[PDB]
Image: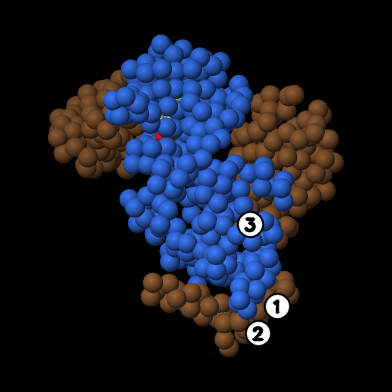
Chain colours: A brown, B blue
């Protein structure tokens, strides 16, 4: 072929552009030889994992949980001295509720699991761990890193989800709103407005309409309140899953 | 004659086994050499059978125009294609075309990258190996940084197919099966002890019933990703537990196709609970009142 030679040449050119001491074919063929004779690296693969997955390696005895080893990458990953970790126990570095899960993964193959570890200079970060069981037993593993309140209703207007902030916004416990119609909390004079909003967001399916109305707090006082809100539809069936609302104390 | 000498020289002075370095044609010796130099070059800017074997994926670095200038050694264990075969070749020649655009966006221009990409796979479930025309598409979870000429340094993890599990499972994960409208057709039975639901209650309920509202949007995108590509890993999200409160889950999911019919039956979810119940004072939903 014609371009066969042309891409072999583009390779050669590419080579000369990357070999800084660097002529003809035999030569660059051999200058490359000497220039790599000067120079994947072992400890560098480590930096690759660190950069890519934000992972660090560690090896812990299976029987006890003893850290027979931790790579220093632990300090960029977890803000931990290598000393703080090495010679320690893996149960020491995980959330207490992850203790059990952890035990199962260390009984007497591949291993893969997720767990909260401690960082610091009491906070936990989630950690994906992979690796395998080698004899010595031990586990060779890598751990990498990864004003208003909101409500959902059925198309009738029944509260079917509120975040705890309703307590701070309107005085009610979530239980005292859940199961009831948002219109039941609406001032008379405004109820038709609220319902117009609810017929409309459903007809104008997808989009956000917003409406204002008074809302009786737990202490009975009428609270002006703006709710922008929109229907949410099922990605497959396009059935209306529910209406999503953000009820902002005006 | 006199060039064949120096080609075998360069080959056996590539970082390769004498074995594999003998066999290379010259275009491959070019490719591999160049990728090795390029790669070393990026490395300066940044700064083993263990790390390699403890990984559940492979490392790869791809230039901004798509050249795959480095692929970790163990890639073959997951894709069947080898480091020697692919090094120096375009990522776009080995990925699903309907992913090419997304890949392009992720090679380009915050530095953190996370997406899913379908790549050619020529190793078979359990051991065996096929030929490049007989190539299946495999979905990979890719996370890394784009970095400065620009590179993308990613780790690519295959998502284990739930029918084929090489890997064991602990008490803190449970399985669930869904209609394509994300309904509950089947659920594991540890779901009770972990969250308190009995499987009966969940069936014919849309999973959207149990998302913390603050999650639902994220979840739909994951779903859409799952349907475009065939597998997915969710971000983390919290499921409304039964007696109030919630739990941190993270699910990987798989549409399973009817093998005779060739249509897709359902979605298999493998569900990783990451926490106990949190904030069980609080009742977020109607379910948590009864
Ligand atoms: C594959 S996925 O995105 O991660 C996913 C996760 C949980 C999913 O439903 C679940 C499964 C579970 F065990 C707890 C919860 C909650 N809350 C939701 C579904 C999916 C799929 O959409 C689906 F459509 F199969 C439904």
Q: Quadrant of ligand 1?
A: top left
Q: Secondary structure at mark 3?
A: helix
Q: Secondary structure at mark 1?
A: helix
Which numbered disc, 1 or 3, marks the residue closer to the eye?
A: 3
The relative height of residue B274 versus residue A180 in the rendered view (above or below) is below
| Distance from Cα at disc 1 to Cα at disc 3 | 21 Å
User: Front-most of A26 and A147?
Assistant: A26
Per the rendering, the mark at residue B20 is 3
Q: Residue furthest front?
A: B1
Per the rendering, the mark at residue A21 is 2
On whether disc 2 and disc 1 are found on a single subunit, the reply is yes
**Position of residue B44 measured from the top left corner of the image (x, y, whole percent):** 66, 70
**Residue drawn at (40%, 47%) of the image:** B133
Q: How many residues crowd mark 2 within 10 Å: few (<14), some (14–19), many (20+)? A: few
**Residue drawn at (24%, 30%) of the image:** A237
**Residue drawn at (62%, 33%) of the image:** A113
Q: Which of disc 1 and disc 2 is earlier in sequence?
A: 2
The relative height of residue A201 versus residue A159 in the rendered view (above or below) is below
On whether disc 2 and disc 3 are found on a single subunit, the reply is no
Disc 2: host chain: A
The relative height of residue B161 versus residue A30 in the rendered view (above or below) is above
Mark 2 touching mark 1, by CB under 8 A?
yes
**Relative side of A66 to A124, left or right:** right
| Distance from Cα at disc 2 to Cα at disc 3 | 28 Å
**Position of residue A185 measured from the top left corner of the image (x, y, whole percent):** 28, 26
Residue topped by disc 1: A34
Q: Residue furthest bottom?
A: A23
Q: What is the total number of numbered labels drawn onto the structure image? A: 3
**Position of residue B30 measured from the top left corner of the image (x, y, whole percent):** 55, 70
Q: Can I make out residue A250 in this image?
A: yes
Q: Quadrant of the N terminus of chain A?
A: bottom left
């Amino acid at each position: 072929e014609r371009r066969r030679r042309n891409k072999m040449t583009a390779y050669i050119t590419e080579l000369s552009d990357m070999v800084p001491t660097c002529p003809d074919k035999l030569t660059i063929l051999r200058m490359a030889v000497s220039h790599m004779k000067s120079l994947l690296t072992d400890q560098e693969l480590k930096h690759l994992i660190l950069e890519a997955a934000d992972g660090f390696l560690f090896i812990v005895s299976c029987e006890t949980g003893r850290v027979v080893y931790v790579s220093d990458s632990v300090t960029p990953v977890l803000n931990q001295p290598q000393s703080e970790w090495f010679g320690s126990t893996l149960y020491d570095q995980v959330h207490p509720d992850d203790v059990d899960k952890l035990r199962e993964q260390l009984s007497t193959s591949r291993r893969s699991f997720i767990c909260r570890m401690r960082c610091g200079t009491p906070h936990f970060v989630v950690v994906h761990c992979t690796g395998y069981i080698k004899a010595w037993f031990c586990l060779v593993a890598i751990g990498r890193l990864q004003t208003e309140f909101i409500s959902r209703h059925n198309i009738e207007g029944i509260f079917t989800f509120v975040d705890h902030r309703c307590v701070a916004t309107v005085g009610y416990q979530p239980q005292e709103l859940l199961g009831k119609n948002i219109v039941e909390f609406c001032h008379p004079e405004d109820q038709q407005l609220l319902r117009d909003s609810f017929q409309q967001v459903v007809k104008l399916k997808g989009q956000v309409l917003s409406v204002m109305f008074r809302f009786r707090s737990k202490t009975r006082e009428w609270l002006w309140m703006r709710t922008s809100s929109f229907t949410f539809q099922n990605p497959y069936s396009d059935e209306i899953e529910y209406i999503i609302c953000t009820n902002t104390n005006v | 004659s006199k060039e064949t000498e120096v080609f075998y020289e360069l080959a056996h002075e590539l970082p390769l086994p004498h074995s594999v370095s003998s066999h290379l044609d010259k275009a491959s010796i070019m490719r591999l050499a160049i990728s090795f130099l390029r790669t070393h070059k990026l490395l300066s800017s940044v700064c083993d059978n263990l790390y390699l074997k403890a990984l559940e994926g492979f490392i790869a670095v791809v230039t901004q125009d798509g050249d795959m200038i480095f692929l970790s050694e163990n890639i073959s264990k997951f894709m069947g294609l080898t480091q020697v075969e692919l090094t120096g070749h375009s990522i776009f020649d080995f990925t699903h075309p309907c992913d090419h655009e997304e890949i392009r966006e992720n090679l380009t221009l915050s530095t953190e990258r996370d997406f899913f990409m379908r790549m050619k796979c020529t190793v078979t479930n359990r051991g065996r190996t096929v030929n490049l025309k007989s190539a299946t598409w495999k979905v990979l979870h890719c996370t890394g940084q784009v970095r400065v000429l620009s590179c993308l340094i990613i780790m690519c993890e295959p998502i284990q197919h739930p029918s084929h599990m090489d890997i064991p499972l602990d008490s803190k994960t449970f399985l669930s099966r869904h209609s394509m409208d994300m309904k509950f057709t089947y659920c594991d039975d540890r779901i009770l002890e972990l969250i308190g639901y009995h499987p009966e209650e969940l069936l014919g309920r849309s999973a959207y019933e149990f998302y913390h509202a603050l999650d639902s949007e994220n979840m739909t995108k994951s779903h859409q990703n799952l349907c475009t590509k065939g597998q997915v890993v969710s971000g983390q999200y919290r499921m409304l537990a039964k007696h109030g409160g919630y739990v941190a889950l993270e699910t990987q999911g798989t549409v399973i196709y009817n093998p005779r019919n060739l249509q897709p039956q359902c979605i298999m979810c493998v569900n990783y609970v990451l926490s106990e119940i949190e904030k069980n004072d609080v009742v977020f939903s109607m379910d948590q009142t009864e």
